[PDB]
Image (cartoon, rainbow, N blue to C red; front, top):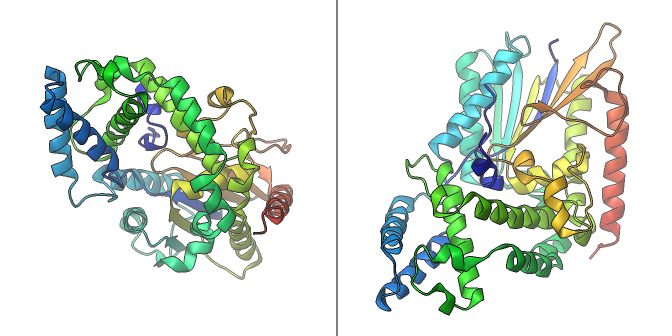
Length: 396
């Protein structure tokens, strides 16, 4: 788990992860994917072609331009698709599940999976389900997807106040000034461009940020090309700090967002609770519910659960990266699993896995990582009521 990989942030590939519950409640981000937009690629290409006609390219700049042109051809028709790596990531997560808990998925167990309408989310769900069925063809499987699940899987598109905050909110100037403070474009552009100092700092900043974006997503495409050495480790460190801050403020518990980015996730936390309550009571006889969606789903959902420190409210932008780390929350294929157990006195316990590692809640338990379900559900219902009160201030 190299330092260079974590600096890819939410573009980091899923990390290496090489008694018996009666129910699993799951939310998983789509696996590693191709870039969704050619804007960054085009920005880099346009700068290098303009410099080539002012004879402003270095030898490395010429090699960079040939490499950008090649990536453009290789990405054509692939934008936003789940990659082969993304497929194998889902197979790894499914495969450890059934290997770790074969009794749960034995005999004729019943599972349900849902996904958004986005193809990479559907393909991720199918990669996961195909691994499941291959290990046990006797499973009973319900498979559905689409805009009917917008309310629980795409709440970030439905809340008018949040949409306005995401596209024009007060986090934007903080982010811009942080980028200006953190990113020094001239040392980077010097490798590629003669006289980078003649570039306006705005243009230079966009070029370097677009180039970082191309380099960060390349390991997710399964294309055997790598661009990490366009930048030093310290430049990747700084780039990651800016992108970590952008994710924190736009999607999580930053004070500037007033917890609006977190509150909008309560319908999914409510559905998690309801589907476990239905299994416990008998209204449902599913052994597992799986859900496939986006990092814009996972990040606020994890904060609203209050998994420790993921909902920290950090006043100072410069301090965020010490306390909140996006690659620890939402790498590619990020996933949350609630594992439910019934002990010898029929009391219900729950373990919370975040990227398959046990997570902590700010409640007490005498046998960590297992929490009383009763205590946990009461705590989550309080988080939901808090979310609704937060949304009452933005009723808009």
